[PDB]
Length: 186
Ligand SMILES: C/C(=C\CCP(=O)(O)OP(=O)(O)O)CO
Image (cartoon, rainbow, N blue to C red; front, side, top):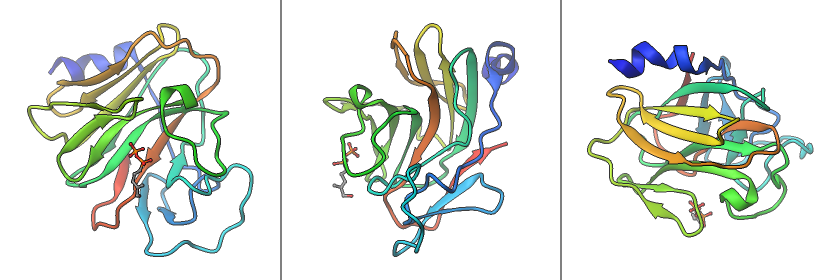
């Protein structure tokens, strides 16, 4: 459809790989650096400054300061996940709420069927079908972050007219221990 035919004409396809140095020690980054899973217990890793030590988050290796970009994430049959972008300057040590005011622009799924935007307050999304693959789209200049069902091209959510100042990283978060991973499409 139009989604497939037009996406690269309008947005530059980002080749996003996960940065193991940023991943919470309870997270496992795959060898090919496209997939993330959760461990039963935290691994023994350094608390280097780049690492999220409280939030179960991991970042992409590269950030954006301009232009239009997109990447796709296979969420599959996961019951829980949150993806989007965050500012380079987010608090990585300890806890703050993942909201736009704290530099996080994400949406996702909890409890198998509760789709929401991580905002203050959180807003519930009504999706006609559960997405298996999600397209994340960034237009830095217009300040739009948009999410689409990457299979049927249907709209999921758009953060509108954000005045971005900082560089933006792709961000990924998983809380649950389940057999299906969260995977970036190349
Ligand atoms: C406290 C907990 C789940 C709630 C996570 P949270 O309070 O940051 O809520 P969220 O950021 O998913 O809207 C147990 O992992």
